[PDB]
Image (cartoon, rainbow, N blue to C red):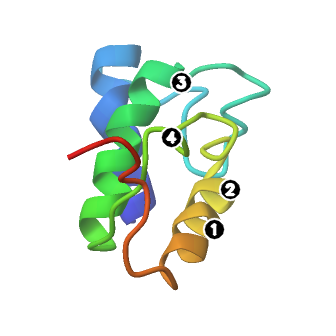
Amino acid sequence: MLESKLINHIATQFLDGEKDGLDSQTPLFELNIVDSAAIFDLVDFLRQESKVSIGMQEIHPANFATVQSMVALVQRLKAHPEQGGAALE
């Protein structure tokens, strides 16, 4: 249900608080519903819950194409200690 919590978050600012075309298993790319702008928000949600950091370099919608894409993107960096902080404080 955590996967629908990241949806309804931006579904407010994007869809007037309605869920249609935008959900976890729904193809965010094929329907083009979510912008790359809201990816930055979906990031904060995932990295916060999973207690990890991700770099802006890795923050792009290609990796957040669906729930199964974005979940697995976090799962790869989970095995890393520290990453993303390149030329950044």
Q: Earlier in the sequence, mark 2 or mark 3?
A: 3
Give the CA separation, mark 2 to mark 1. Answer: 5 Å
> What element does badge 4 sit on?
loop
Q: Residue 82 location, x and y as percent?
A: 37, 72
> What element does badge 3 sit on?
loop
- Quarter of the rendering containing residue 29: top right
Q: Residue 47 location, x and y as percent?
A: 33, 61
Give the CA separation, mark 2 to mark 4. Answer: 12 Å
Inspect the image, locate mark 2, and give the three-letter code of the amino acid beneath it. Ser
Inspect the image, locate mark 3, and give the three-letter code of the amino acid beneath it. Val
Give the CA separation, mark 4 to mark 3. Answer: 14 Å
The residue pinned by badge 2 equals: 69
Q: Earlier in the sequence, mark 1 or mark 4?
A: 4
Q: Earlier in the sequence, mark 1 or mark 3?
A: 3
Q: Looking at this view, is 21 or 33 the one in front?
A: 33
The residue pinned by badge 3 equals: 34
Give the CA separation, mark 1 to mark 3. Answer: 19 Å
Q: Earlier in the sequence, mark 2 or mark 4?
A: 4
Q: Looking at this view, is 80 or 65 the one in front?
A: 80
Residue at 46% over, 33% down: 39
Report the mark closest to the observer, 4 or 3.
Answer: 4
Inspect the image, locate mark 4, and give the three-letter code of the amino acid beneath it. Ile
Report the mark closest to the observer, 1 or 4.
Answer: 4
Give the CA separation, mark 2 to mark 3. Answer: 14 Å
* Residue lying furthest bottom: 79
Decide: marks 2, 1 in contact (CB < 8 A)?
A: yes
Rendered image: mark on residue 59: 4
Rendered image: mark on residue 72: 1
Report the mark closest to the observer, 1 or 3.
Answer: 1
Above or below: residue 21 compared with residue 78: above
Decide: marks 1, 4 in contact (CB < 8 A)?
A: no
